[PDB]
Image 1 (spheres, each protein chain N blue to C red):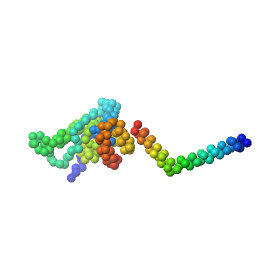
Image 2 (cartoon, helix red, strand yellow):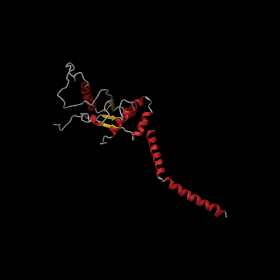
Image 3 (tube, chains in turn red, yellow):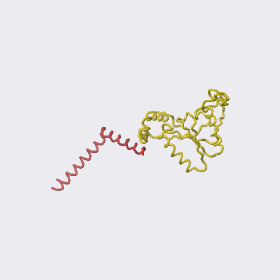
Image 4 (cartoon, chains in turn red, yellow):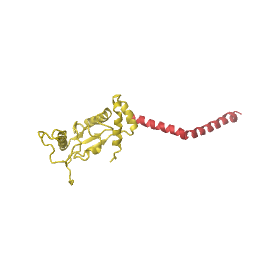
Length: 48
Length: 165
């Protein structure tokens, strides 16, 4: 009961959530925010 | 009728073109640090000369002798062409002495401005990678440069758009 009910379901929940977070990162609106972050960091390195 | 040979200094003088405009803080320290290292590392073999006068009026096919004497009271006799021409050969003696020399000219800010003359010097280009960093780089000096910032960006990209060659 513990292994199937508690440890196996926890494995699927982590598995399904992790897949969803990977897909959310590559969304167009999310990628553009990261691209802005990368450019802003490149300025800071050169400016220093 | 360009001659096949041109008279140039035996040793090439070195001119450093600033990021945007010489005579301003951002460029001045941007040049000063390099000038110090030239003094220190190569001490005893490099002499530094600073010319406050202009150098862009160095012409060889204008006339035989424009304004030969200061008593002619001519337009060019009392103009600034007299000392500019007198400083042209000043570089030559330094070049014949084999001791390396630079040009701390505060008026030239573009490579072709001093490319048609007989100096034909080594041009060293110091540039910021992007205009975005340069703008905030000017901001660090203070409010004094904020009055003059706008024209300090137009002088940058005009120098940038020049071909790297």
